[PDB]
Image (cartoon, rainbow, N blue to C red):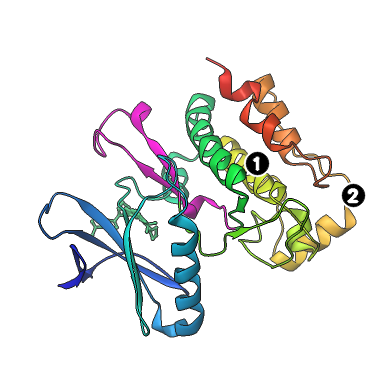
Amino acid sequence: TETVGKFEFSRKDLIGHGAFAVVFKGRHRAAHDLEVAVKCINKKNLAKSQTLLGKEIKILKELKHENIVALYDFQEMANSVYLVMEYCNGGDLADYLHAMRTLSEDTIRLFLQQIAGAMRLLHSKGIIHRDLKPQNILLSNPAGRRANPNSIRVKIADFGFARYLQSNMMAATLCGSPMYMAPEVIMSQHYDGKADLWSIGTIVYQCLTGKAPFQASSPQDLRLFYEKNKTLVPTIPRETSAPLRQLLLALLQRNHKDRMDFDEFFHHPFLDAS
Ligand SMILES: CC(=O)NCC(=O)N1[C@@H]2CC[C@H]1c1ccc(Nc3ncc(C(F)(F)F)c(NC4CCC4)n3)cc12
């Protein structure tokens, strides 16, 4: 048992591992039924892990929303950093999609309404996430794992690559997962918040079809494909509802200037459909 302020965890209770973070399930020391996810340095990449966890704190301390994984507390010291986060009892969308293969349009709508809500807050604060992928979309059912799936709440996680972007500036750091990167990101161009909208379009397309809209053998191959193809049209299955078709087509615009803007996303007919 290690303690971080009012919370405790055992390194036995590993729930996830990446190059730059290790995450343990923990609990409040007084309210043992309050589950938490404790994110810790990966000492294999000490300096970068410490930097990214510190940036995550800096960003998440400004973001309170149902659909953003909550930061309950944190502890930054000279040689280590902890984040005590909301525990999402449903795990990640990558694993959920692996088991479900594809999601109904109604489930995609429920999830995307929640992602849109979180993105409204990021956009209003001037923050871009830059690492949206299914592994960073977490699921939580307030009625418990075995409850009605209509009750699944979605939370954006992993803000270590996030930044403020001034409205007259562009970003240029290579961030994210290549299969979810906007073309402008993987082509090492300048980009803005619309790069996240491409990532969201890729996630929605994967939910709908079970595959990438633009398949490639490697990140290098995907970059070459984007470089060579100045128009990108995803194949929309003919059973797709018109609002979801139009949402996908507008998000998966190769050129960020042509891509759906945030106001269009937040008010998209797909999101207000019954
Ligand atoms: C010991 C135990 O109870 N294990 C549960 C477990 O391993 N599960 C449960 C269901 C699938 C997998 C899993 C992964 C992640 C979560 N929850 C969660 N909540 C918050 C965070 C976060 F706050 F840290 F983001 C988080 N991050 C992990 C690292 C891989 C995704 N995971 C829950 C689970």
Taking the image as shown, residue 226 lies to the left or right of residue 196, namely: right
Q: Are marks 2 and 1 in contact (CB under 8 Å)?
A: no
| Location of residue 179 in the rendering, given as x and y in whole percent from the top left corner | 65, 56
Mark carried by residue 201: 1
Q: Amino acid at mark 1?
A: Gly
> Which disc is residue 230 wearing?
2
Indicate the position of residue 27 as horizontal and vertical percent values: 18, 58
Residue 110 is one of the magenta-drawn residues = no
Q: Position of residue 79 (x, y in %)?
A: 36, 85
Q: Which segment did they paint magenta? A: 131-156
* Whole-number angstrom distance, CA of label 2 to CA of label 1: 18 Å
Query: Badge 2, how many Cα within 10 Å: few under 14, some, many 20+?
Result: few
In the foreground, 81 or 113? 81
Residue beneath the point at 86% across and 59% down:
227
Q: Quadrant of ligand 1?
A: bottom left
Q: Secondary structure at mark 2?
A: loop
Query: Does 72 sit above or below residue 202?
Result: below
Query: Is residue 134 in the magenta section?
Result: yes
Residue in the foreground of this view, choosing between 41 and 77: 77
Is the N terminus in the top left, top right, bottom left or bottom right quadrant? bottom left
